[PDB]
Length: 474
Ligand SMILES: [Zn+2]
Image (cartoon, rainbow, N blue to C red; front, side, top):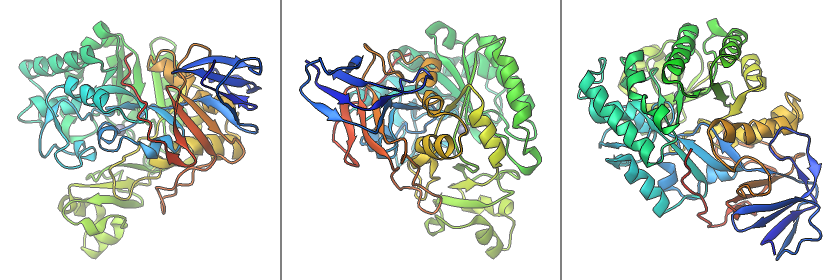
């Protein structure tokens, strides 16, 4: 007998096919059957008429490394239908690094002395011992590696330092890491050469992991950054994942046509993937960057001046008698939201076939970017339903089947007999992102229930207490 059957709803199986009326039976942590299950005995037959039953959403781009440990409920994500998170992005991973004051943007994961894992395996062991509500597919970050090995980050790494970082990366992969990420855009790795990155990532071919990247530049020099990324992919001979693809800065608006063409062309000869979030504003460490600071900028948190959280940077700068660019140093370390993208480009990138959905949520932020709480429902509701950017099955595929495939998450991402029971029950008519920049932590609408490995983690708009997530391996 099945533990339960989700009956009377419409199944969108995650294979990018129109939904069909069918029941979904679960036994233990597996989807036992799909279709007319009236003849199957079940201990519970849950009515989900008028709802869609889809695979659990897989957040392809998170910075939930530490949040998984400190807030196992993972409410920001399960409330949106997320059942699996990919961590350690943009070269930023919680482990391996024992440091009381890690360099920005590593501080985006810190809650105070959070970087206490000397070995990547220690981190994974911690997760397994006290599992979060969602599954975790963890990558090790190149910048974290640099911080752990290099006494001076403002230069290229020596052969010895590269050897030290490669050893840590190899141990991480051996321990279960699904890949290695880089973020040469940030200070810790700005001086890292392409060759350094290649040598440190050599182990990916041996362990079969992926190379993920926050490209060196996403504006004026994005073509060069894209070419570097493709080159790295060819040298390593592993799948590459371009993180939160965008074209930032007014001088680059409309260039998504150009970048997507280059990416599509690359996909014809090598393994390339990409993800993006559904918003026109970015968010990360407060940084002295003339493009990031060109437009509206909001502070998400501020160490030296906590009372600045939520304030508009232009106001702060103007009142301190300086430009936003010049006032940044005295406010660091801090975080911010940057309105530097254009809706047309965001829509073009989301619509681009292969683009997976990734939130890039920064969970520890005092006044966070709403993507942390509304990314997935925003794609399913606002973009798919209300704007018709793509049919619902395609929007679902972009956050389930496609993603599971690109990250090698076996037996997940599809509503298929035999696959793991990571599932979401949502109302296609009402699903919507409630989080706004003004109120960035509002729970999404239309999310009925969420299951991870068969156990309900989200029901009646609350965490059930089921710490059902598992550390996954590629
Ligand atoms: Zn990034």
